Image (cartoon, rainbow, N blue to C red; front, top):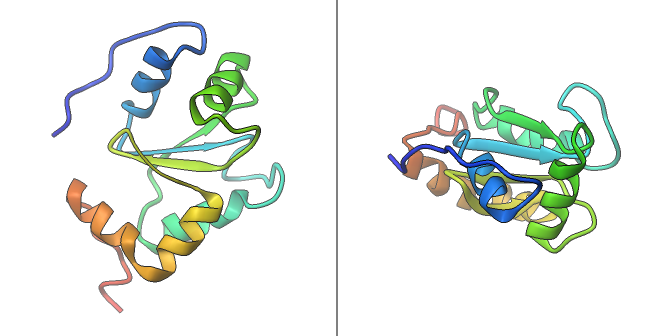
Length: 121
C-alpha cells in the first residue's frame, strides 16, 4: 500500500499529514458521526454507509485546538466536513455531494481495494 504514519507536532502540516495517514477513510468534522454538530455532518456518513464504509476514523476537530486550527489552516478554510482517502484530498461535504451521484468516489474506493455496496444492487 502507501506506507504508515509516525510524525507529531502542534497542528503542523507534517502532523496533519500523519493524521490523514492513520486510516484509508479519515473523516473530519467539527463534531461526531453520532450527534449532528451543525449542518452537513450526516451527509458524509450517509454517503459512506450507503457505499458500505462504516469503519472510517471520524475525527472530531473540537476535541483538540491543534486538530481545529491545524485542519482550518491545512485546508485554508474556516469550516468543512471532509474525507481523505489514502491520505489524499478527495473532498469537502459540498464536493462529496457531486461526486457520489456522478460515481467518481467509486473509482477512488477501487484504488484502495474497497467495494461500493451500490455495485450489488
